[PDB]
Image (tube, grey):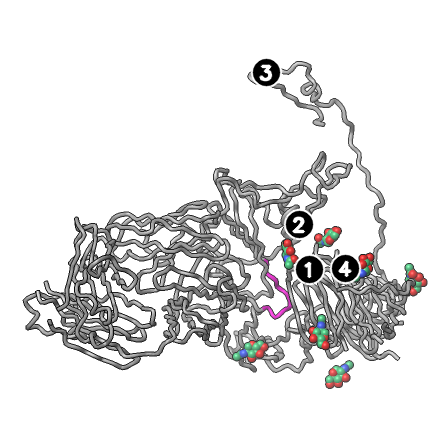
Amino acid sequence: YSVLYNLAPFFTFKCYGVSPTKLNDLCFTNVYADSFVIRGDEVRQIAPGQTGNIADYNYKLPDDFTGCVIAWNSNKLDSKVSGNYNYLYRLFRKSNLKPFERDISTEIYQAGNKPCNGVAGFNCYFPLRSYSFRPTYGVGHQPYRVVVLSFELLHAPATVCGPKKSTNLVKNKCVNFNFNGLKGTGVLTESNKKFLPFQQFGRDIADTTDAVRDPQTLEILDITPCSFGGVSVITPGTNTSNQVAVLY
Amino acid sequence: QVQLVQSGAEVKKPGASVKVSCKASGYPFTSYGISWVRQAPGQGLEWMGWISTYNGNTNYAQKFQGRVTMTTDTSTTTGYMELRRLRSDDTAVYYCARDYTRGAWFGESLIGGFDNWGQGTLVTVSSASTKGPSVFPLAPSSKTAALGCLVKDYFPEPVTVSWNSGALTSGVHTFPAVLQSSGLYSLSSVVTVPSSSLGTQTYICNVNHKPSNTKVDKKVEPK
Amino acid sequence: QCVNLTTRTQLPPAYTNSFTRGVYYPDKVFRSSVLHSTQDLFLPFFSNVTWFHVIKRFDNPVLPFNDGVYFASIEKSNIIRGWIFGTTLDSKTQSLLIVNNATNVVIKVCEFQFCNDPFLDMESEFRVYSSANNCTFEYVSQPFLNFKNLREFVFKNIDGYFKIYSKHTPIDLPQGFSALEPLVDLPIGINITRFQTLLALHRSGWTAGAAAYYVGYLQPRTFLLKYNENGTITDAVDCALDPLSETKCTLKSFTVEKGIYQTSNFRVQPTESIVRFPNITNLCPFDEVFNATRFASVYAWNRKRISNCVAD
Amino acid sequence: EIVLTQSPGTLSLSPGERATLSCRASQTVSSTSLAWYQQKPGQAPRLLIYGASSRATGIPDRFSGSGSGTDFTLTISRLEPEDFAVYYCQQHDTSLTFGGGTKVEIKRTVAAPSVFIFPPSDEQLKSGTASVVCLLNNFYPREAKVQWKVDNALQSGNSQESVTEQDSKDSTYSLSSTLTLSKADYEKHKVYACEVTHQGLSSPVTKSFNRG
Ligand SMILES: *[C@@H]1O[C@H](CO)[C@@H](O)[C@H](O)[C@H]1NC(C)=O
Ligand SMILES: *[C@@H]1O[C@H](CO)[C@@H](O)[C@H](O)[C@H]1NC(C)=O
Ligand SMILES: *[C@@H]1O[C@H](CO)[C@@H](O)[C@H](O)[C@H]1NC(C)=O
Ligand SMILES: *[C@@H]1O[C@H](CO)[C@@H](O)[C@H](O)[C@H]1NC(C)=O
Ligand SMILES: *[C@@H]1O[C@H](CO)[C@@H](O)[C@H](O)[C@H]1NC(C)=O
Ligand SMILES: *[C@@H]1O[C@H](CO)[C@@H](O)[C@H](O)[C@H]1NC(C)=O
Ligand SMILES: *[C@@H]1O[C@H](CO)[C@@H](O)[C@H](O)[C@H]1NC(C)=O
C-alpha cells in the first residue's frame, strides 16, 4: 500500500477500522475491491450509517465496515461533449438494498396499484436513470470513480499482507514474537496438542491465545509467559539496622 | 532498471518452426504480460499477440491464429515463442515488449502501452546455402575522381566492409543491400578521391564474412 | 441431449425425527476440556426432517434452500452422486453444481440450462444440461466418498460464502452424537433458494438400488458444546428445547441439583399497529391557484404566498 | 477491424521548428486507448505518450499529445538532431492495431548530384554476366528519377536501386543503380546511357559510355 499516492490529487480517502498511515503490517484473509462511478454530490453517501438514493438503491455499506474508500474525480476520461449515458443508477425500488448486494432488476416499477403490463405508462417509471455526464456540469455533477476496499479478518491462514521478511524460529526462551500479524511476548515450546488440519490456533479456559501454528511448517507451538512473581522485603526498624532479607 | 534480452538470428529454411526466447530482468515477471510484435524491412509495425504471466491466458491475431504459440516459465522468468509453418514473408525484426494494455490477473484493458521493448530478433528466410563473397573492383574512367568495390553472392546478410582499415573512412559510401530473384545478396562501396591521386595513393577494399570466415581484400586501381 | 422419463412413484414423503444430529464445529479455534456457549445456525434437536426413499421409486423434487440445509444419506454402493443449487435454474441467473461421480469432486459455478429432470445413469450417459454460458469459479479435488454407509452434510450460504461440512460413518436416523468437521469453503456469492439431488441409476430400463436421503432445515439458536481432553465435541445442549435444557445452559453444566432456579423472563409481543393523527383541516389554497378561471400572462405572472395550512 | 491513418506521409523540417503529426481513426476510439511511439533507425521503438495526453517516464517535456473523438495530434515544440525518427500511433480499443509510420526528415537547401557511370570490370567478361553501375552523389531533395537506355530507347525491369539514409554531416542522399545482363547480349551492344532527372537540376542529364 506504500505506492498509492501516485495518481491525480485524491478528493476522498477515508479509512474505517485501520489507520492508512504506514500500516501495511496487517495480514488479511481476502480483499474485496468494489469499483463504480458516481457524482460528486453522492460521494458522501458511501460511508457507514449513511442514507441516500445510492445508499439504499445502489450500494450500501455496513455499519461495522472494516476497510476504506478512495474516490477521485475522473472528468478528463468519463466526460464527453455529446454526453455519456453509459453510466446508470437505480432511483425506484420497492425495498432498500441489503449491504453488499447487487440489484440488476429490469422489471417496471409498480408505482400505483394498476399493473404496468411490461411497458412504459402511467404510474410506471423505469428503474434505471441516466447520469448524463458532461464536462460543462458543476463540481457536484462531475463524474467520480470510487474504489472501496474491504478487508477480511478471520481465523484463517490470512495470506495477504505486506513485504515483511521472516526470521529463524527459536524456542525455550522468552522472546518477542510476531506470528502472522499476531504480536506477543513469551516462550514458545513444542506442543503436544491434537490439532486438526483445519484448525489454526488454540485457546485456554482464560480465553486467551495459548497455542499457535507455524505458517511455514505444520508445527504446533505452546506459548507461555516468561517467569514472574512477587518480592517482599523483610527488615527490622531502620533505627536498629540497615540489613534486609528478600522473599521471592 | 528493467532489462529485456532476446535470442540470435536464424537462417532456417521455409516451412520449419521458429523458436524465440525473451528474458526479463529487474521487474516482477508475473505482474506483467508479454506482447509479440514484428516489423518488416521497408514496412511498418505489425502486432501479433499477447500472453498473460499469471495463468497463461493468451490473445492471438487472426492472421497468425494457426501458427503462433506463446508460453512462459516463471523459474527462469523466460517467455517462449514457437511459430510453425514459417514462410518467406516472415523475414523481419521481432520485438518482445512488456504489456501494459491488458492486465494479467483480470484480463481487462488498462491505460498504457508497450513501455519497454527488447533488443529485437532478426528472422531471415531463404532456401539457399551460404557462399563466399565475390568481389569486383570498379576503376575510374580514363578521362573529383570516383571508384568502388562491388560484392555479390555473399550469404548471409552480415558482412563488413573496410577501406584501408579505416584510414579513409570519411568518403566511403555503402548502399543498402539488395536481393535478387536467386536469393543472393548484393552490396557496393564507393570511394571518392582527388583526381591527382589515382596513380599514387593506394586504395584497397576489404570484405569480411564471419559465417564463411573470409577476410578477402583487393587493390582497386584505374584501368 | 435430454431423456424423457416420468415413471416416478408419486407418494407423500415420509417425516422422521432428527434427535441430536446436525452438530458441526462452529470455528477453527482449538479448545479442550471446556464448555462453550455459541449462537449460530444449527439443526434443532428432535426436529421433523423429511425422508425420501429411492428404489420403481424415483423421486427427485426440487426442495427449498432456506438459511441452511442438513442432508443425510443412508446408502450402500454409492447411488447418490451430487447436487445442484440455484434460484431459477436457467441461464437468467447463476447456478452452482457439484458432482462426485466416484472419480473426483468437481464444482461448477456458471449459467446452466437444465432439463425437467437432470440426473445421471460402466458410466457413459450424462444427461443433465445442454448449454454452457459464462463461468465464474471452478474446483477439483479428492472425492468426498443391510445399508452400511451414513453420510452427513451441512450446507450454508452466508455473506455470499458457501460452507460445506461433512462426516462419514458406517452403520430412521440412528441415535447418537457425531460432530461434522468442516470440509469446503467457497467465495461464490450466489443467490440460492432451491436445490435438487443427483442420482445415478443402474441400467439393466434401469433398477435403482435401495437408498434413503433426509433433509432438514437450520435455524438460529444458542447451543452449549462440551469438549473432552482432545479437541472433539462430545455432547451438546440446545438452550431452547425445554425448561430443563435452558436451566442447564443457565447453570453452565450438564447436571442440575435439587432446587428452584430463576431461569429467565417472559413477555408478550404486540400483534397489530395503529397510528393516530389529528385531521386534515384548513387545506392550503392549491385549488384556488390551479383552478383560477383567468390566468395572467407570462410577463405578469401572478405570485402568491401560502402558509399555515396542510400541503396536500 | 479499425484502421489508423497517419498524416503526413513525410515531413521536411529543420532542427528548431515545430512538428505536428496527425492520426485519424475510421471509427470512434477512446482517448485512453491511444499511444504514440517513436522508433529511431537502429533501435527498438520506445513509448512516449499513453492515453493521448500523458507523458511516459524518461520522455522530454517538449513532446506532447492531444486530440478527441477521431482525430489526435502529437506536438513537438522544438526539433533536435536526434528527434528524426519514425512515428507510430497505436489504438487498442478494439483488438489492437498499429500505424504505417510517419517519417520526419531534415529539410535543407536544394543541391545537385554528381551522377557518374561505371562500366563492368574485365573479370566479369569471363563470368558470363556483366554489371554496370550508375552512381548519384550528394543531392537534395531525395526525389530523383533514374533510367537506363541501351542506345535506342528506355529500359526497365533488369535494374536494382539502392538509396541510403539521411547523411550525418550534409544530410544528403546517395543513390546506386545496378544493371546486370549476360555477356551474349552484352556484346550485342556498345553504347549505353544512364539518365537522371532531379529537381535541383534545371534539365535532365544523360551520361553515355561505349566499350573501352
Ligand atoms: C513455503 O510455505 C509452505 C507452506 O506450507 C511450506 O510447506 C514450505 O516449506 C515453505 N518453504 C520454505 C522454503 O520455507
Ligand atoms: C420431453 O418432455 C418435454 C415435456 O413437455 C417435451 O417438451 C419434450 O418434447 C420431450 N422430449 C425431449 C427430447 O425433450
Ligand atoms: C412432526 O413430528 C411429529 C412427531 O415426530 C409428527 O407427529 C408430526 O406429524 C410432524 N409434523 C408434521 C407436519 O407432519
Ligand atoms: C465422471 O467419471 C469419469 C471417470 O469415470 C471422469 O472422467 C469424469 O470427469 C467424471 N465426471 C464428473 C462430472 O465428475
Ligand atoms: C455472458 O453474459 C452475457 C450477458 O452478461 C450474455 O449475453 C452472453 O450470452 C453470456 N455468454 C454466453 C456464452 O452465453
Ligand atoms: C434471490 O432471488 C429472489 C427471486 O425473486 C429474490 O426475491 C431475492 O431477493 C434474491 N436474493 C437476494 C439476496 O437478492
Ligand atoms: C484422547 O486422545 C488420547 C490420545 O492417546 C486417547 O488415548 C483417548 O482415548 C482420547 N479420548 C479421551 C476421551 O481421552
Return the x and y of residue C117 as percentages of the image width and height: 80, 63
* Residue C307 in picture, x, y percent from top left: 66, 23
Q: Report the magenta stretch's main SS.
A: loop
Quarter holding residue C291: top right
Residue A119 as seen in the image, left or right of residue B121: right
Task: Give how far apart the Cα atoms at labels 3 and 4 are.
Answer: 65 Å
Q: Which mark is residue B180?
A: none
Q: Residues within 10 Å of mark 1 (few under 14, many from 20)?
A: many
Q: Nearer the viewer, mark 3 or mark 1?
A: 1
Q: Are marks 1 and 4 in contact (CB under 8 Å)?
A: no
Instruction: From the image, tell me which residue sits under label 1.
Output: C111
Q: Which residue, given by chain and number where applicable, does mark 2 sit on?
A: A104
Residue most extreme to the top:
C294
Label whose residue precedes the other's in the sequence (3 or 1): 1
Q: Tag 4 or tag 3, which sits nearer the N-term? A: 4
Residue at image coords 15%, 75%: B204
Check if residue A110 falls in the magenta segment: no
What crowding class fits label 3: few (fewer than 14 Cα within 10 Å), some (14-19), or many (20 or more)? few
Please, what secondary structure does the residue beneath circle 2 have? loop
Q: Is mark 1 within 8 Å of ligand 5?
A: yes
Amino acid marked by disc 4: Asp
Which amino acid lies under the numbered mark 2 shown in the image of this protein? Ile
Q: Looking at the image, is B183 positioned above or below residue D142? A: below
Label 1 vs label 2, nearer the camera: 1
Residue C297: numbered disc: 3
| Residue count near mark 4 (Cα–Cα under 10 Å), binned few <14, some 14–19, many ≥20 | some
